[PDB]
Structure formats: structure tokens, C-alpha cells
Image (cartoon, rainbow, N blue to C red; front, side, top):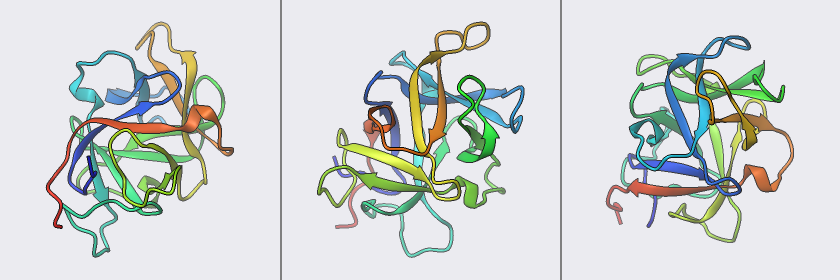
Length: 181
């Protein structure tokens, strides 16, 4: 259950049970970058993310991710980074959450602080967490607000500034690399 750097995870929205999801299609407005949504179905390779450190650092694959760590989530299928910035999200006009760059292109807008809700010190499967975007201070957020025509039935994912029930997430369905000890 200990989630280590290098591990593959799904991230489930606690309230709606939808999974953090991406795919090879951009937003029409805001940044025009690759879009990110909440996806309800269980079988979906597009729901997998790799937990990574920021490139400068001592943290390595197999190290436990700590509460308070700055992390990156890289989409397995497209290699783009979970990203935010000051653009309007398409449904609710909150902070746009996108997929940015690739293996040669990452910036600080790819940085999220892991906040474990209890007194837990290392990230585990099924524990309640928030992810706070470093640059904007937006909490990764979803809700029962859905696209209709393209990607219909999938939920908006965005960033908001207050802690709420709709910004708690749980890591699930993961493959966790062995603990360096």
C-alpha cells in the first residue's frame, strides 16, 4: 500500500468516484493544451499516471512519497504532465487543469503538493489526500459537471482555492514499486 516514486496509480475523486483521466485531445479555449477529465469506467489505460519527483532532487524511484512532497503526475499513455495555470476551465470558469509538455518539456506548472488529510506521513492507497498546485495554489478539484458532445458523461476537472469535499482524492488500482526500505 505504500506509494513510491515510479509507481503507476489511478486517482479517484472521493465524492463522485470518477477517475483522473487524459487523452489525445485539446481544450478548445483557455490554454488550448491537452484536456483532463473525470472518467467513470474501471477499464481505461488513459486513467494511469506515474508518480514522479521534481528533476532537481534526492527523491528516487522506490522512495515513499511524503506528506508535503512536491510531485509530478505523468500520464502514462501520452507522456504529458498534470498541469495548471491561470486559464479558465471550460465549464465552471475555475482554474484550468491540463496535460502539458512531454518527456523533454516540463516546468514548475507541473508541480503539485501532496497533502495527506490525516496524520499519515507517507502516501498510501485509499488514504484521503489533496493535491495543491504549487504555482496557483489551486486544489485539484472535480464535481458532477459533465461534458456532453465530445467526451460526454466525463466530468470537468479544475482547480479551486478552498478545501472542500469535492477536492479530496484517493490513490487506487496502483502498481507500487518496492520500498527502498
